[PDB]
Each structure stands twice: as C-alpha cells, then as structure tokens.
Length: 106
Image 1: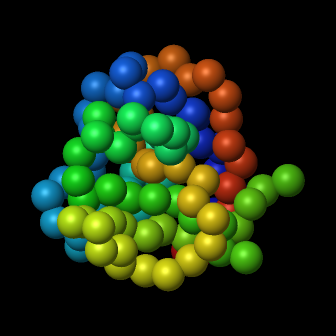
Image 2: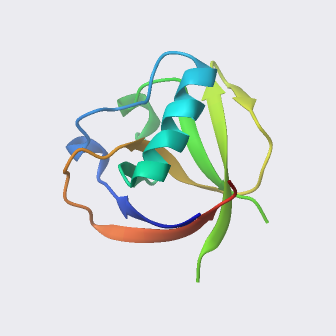
Image 3: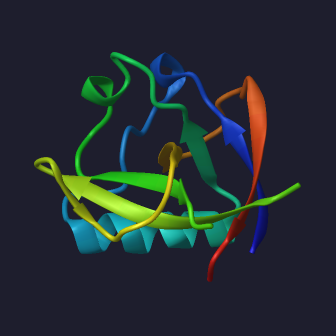
C-alpha cells in the first residue's frame, strides 16, 4: 500500500522487465511491489528502447502519491490512469539515485 520505490538508472538495471505477456507483467509487478523488490525507472528520451516489453507503468491514479498500474505492449495500453511516474522493473540490488513514495491502489 504505502511504498518507497528505489529510482534506478536504466543502464544499471539487470532484469529489464517482468515477463512476456500483459497479464504476466502486471501480476509480477504487483507481486514485486508487495515483496519490496520493485524498482522505478523514470521515462526520458531513450529509456524505453533499453527496457523489455510489455512495460509496466506506474501512473498517478488521482507525501505518498496514489498510483495505479498500466501495462503497454505494441503501443496499446491496458488500464487507464493519469500521469506516468515511471516504468517498473525488478530490483535485484542496484543502487538507486532517489526514492519515490507511492500509495499503490491495492
């Protein structure tokens, strides 16, 4: 529910997505958020081509930001929500540059 997500530099990320289908990446992202093993990469130019699809975005749903998960594959998004805060990735020990406090609608 209340989470502080480590913000990772894209070139440091070891595991660059959660899986191979929309349903799987949403499931795995939720599991990693629950387990405290989820990182956040901020979306800047050149970032997404360095990550693996389907993407899982964390989006503002409405000092902890209420967020919802939205997946994207082939330019189609699954879920509808607000401003993108970043793309979620597994965290396997990478050193963050910041944290993002979020309230995951769960």
